[PDB]
Image: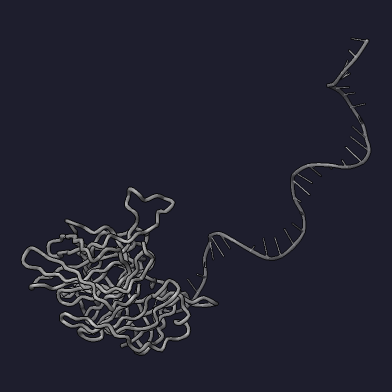
Amino acid sequence: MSLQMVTVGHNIALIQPGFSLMNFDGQVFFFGQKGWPKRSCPTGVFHFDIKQNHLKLKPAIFSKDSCYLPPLRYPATCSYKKHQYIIHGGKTPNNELSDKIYIMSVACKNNKKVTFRCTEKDLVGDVPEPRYGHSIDVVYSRGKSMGVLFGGRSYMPSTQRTTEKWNSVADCLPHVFLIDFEFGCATSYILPELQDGLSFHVSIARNDTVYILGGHSLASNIRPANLYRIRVDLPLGTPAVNCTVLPGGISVSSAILTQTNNDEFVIVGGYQLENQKRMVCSLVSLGDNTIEISEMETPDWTSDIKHSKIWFGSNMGNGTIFLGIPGDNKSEAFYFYTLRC
DNA sequence: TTTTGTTAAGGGCTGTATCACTGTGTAAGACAGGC
């Protein structure tokens, strides 16, 4: 794992905590810019290309049949296999939470210049309340595909919300949501094993299962060291969901996850306590019914990283993470690194 | 029969309206990078 500093072009201000990166056919893209999109890039979607440790953000265009989704911070994202990206929830530049779900796909790649399709999917049934900091992944069971959504935070319900605490947030009830994108429907499942709310956790999806790692629970103000396996079977039109607690769970919120090889993932970064950062790294190796979490060699962090109180980042896709920390003195607002695996 | 106003010309304290003067905030422009 080699750490490398990155320089940024004129529009560095766009990058903020809560941003996301999506990878299409090796090409990386950036979404969730700070502020509302400007004339320079009306979509809020950017080619995110790092050449010789220099990062350029170049505006990307939408197809004629696209939505223009608002920039979203801490939305739930996953990748769907004809490869597309699912974005659900998040905070908008006006601090509202969206209940909408957007789908990003490549509409046209002409002479290495990508046009995107952003389509909004209506959701009916048990729609999950607007959220941020929650997970969504795709499971495959019995030749059928289903979305699994869990966790996050939201504002108080319209009945109890008051202007003195107008921005107060609470964890959502820990109901797993099965989401059929084909029909646009959502079903909620209460499980006894998920008693507490959880947000900013990590989710790993393999076949018919999603594992839930770390995260932070507001009510207890704990980052629990639990690992949850959630299995989904889809026999015809009657889905079934079952959860199992598995000991050996890491305790981490806001960690970043990257795939280094099939059935092996690396977990880097995050927070172990409010004032402490998780400097260690984990390797997760997947079996068809087993999951293994092993400590790995901690990278050669610089002193700036070691002493930073906050860091934020995203997975670039090619086993490489894009990281960031703030700096004061004279000078830059943010300093960015790329950690390879 | 007892209190006040009043005239005119004119003489000091007092109150406020400027002086001159510059730093400084805001904004009207100019300008140059998007390797």
Front-lying residue, A300 or A272 = A272
Front-lying residue, A304 or B10 = A304
Residue at x-position 36% and y-position 62%:
A219
Front-lying residue, A155 or A20 = A155
The relative height of residue A125 versus residue A58 in the rendered view (above or below) is above
Q: Quadrant of residue A207?
A: bottom left
User: At which x and y percent is residue A113?
Assistant: 25, 78
Q: How many marks?
A: 0
Front-lying residue, A248 or A168 = A248
Q: Quadrant of residue A85?
A: bottom left
Image quarter (top left, top right, bottom left or bottom right) of the C terminus of chain A: bottom left
User: At which x and y percent is residue A287?
Assistant: 18, 83
Residue at x-position 54% and y-position 77%:
A329
Residue at x-position 32% and y-position 86%:
A295
Q: Quadrant of residue A340?
A: bottom left
User: At which x and y percent is residue A38?
Assistant: 36, 66
User: At which x and y percent is residue A266?
Assistant: 29, 83
Question: Is residue A59 something one can see in this rendering?
Answer: no
Can you name the residue that lies furthest to the front here? A247
Image quarter (top left, top right, bottom left or bottom right) of the N terminus of chain A: bottom left
Color style of the picture: one colour
Residue at x-position 31% and y-position 73%:
A214
Question: Is residue A300 something one can see in this rendering?
Answer: yes
The relative height of residue A4 versus residue A180 in the rendered view (above or below) is below
